[PDB]
Length: 330
Image (cartoon, rainbow, N blue to C red; front, side):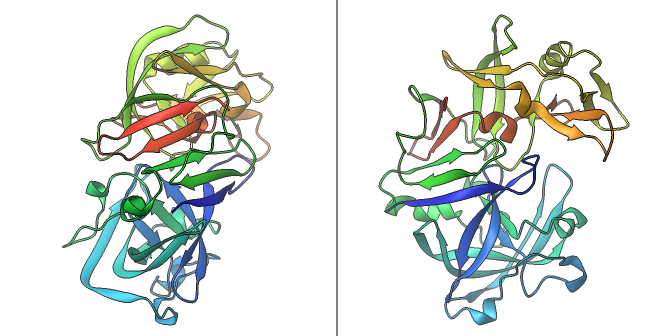
């Protein structure tokens, strides 16, 4: 089997992407944030504290003839941005782009933190990291991909995120029309439960390529590109007036600037992030200070190849017995 679903930016900055997901019988369609950096499929629901729901579409398991309470199971998750959610668990039928999994753990939120409430466009998350990170207790549950894998034509999914435009998540096949050149594959460590890999270096603008190993994660659920302070300083030094602002929480730059591109290495291959992808607009409405899309990972504890990086590529998440990651230009 295969599946193919369009993923759409939630706003004009590509702060996140939502993909429609069918849950239950009859189908209830929720728009979920597909997150290769976590491993829980959780939704706003009829059980979510009412004051914490503001515009989201909810899953109502009592209206699904295939929903079953997973007795005694609870979940609780905290994300790198400080947000969190928790609740109980149902199993139900879940379909993405025509690909159907029966008995998928659907984690129903009883509580969500303010940033979730405040984002009316995201109805929940669909985790696509390794199932070892799933938070369900006392019986850990599998991701949608893990459950689908055996049925797929090939044990892969691909992320093709758009810049200020829709893109695609495919399951079970590689669309050879969706990228240019060849796909370069690179080793993955699953030791931390992430799609963790080592970039071979970087260049700023038309500058020379610096060969250096940068371990990080391919994370569709993180907006920006978080890299070591040395790398980030080298990038922003090429933008007149750019500076790190403790009050804003990262590098800012004059909105009048034209940003240089940023290249990262995948083996001997190179992915080029155009300068415009690195512009996240005014820090506050009407400001002439703009927020940068490349930020330091210092104090995160891990480098993160988030959407800024991934959207410059066609990315293969190869879930074969020994997982790997593939990157192509597009």
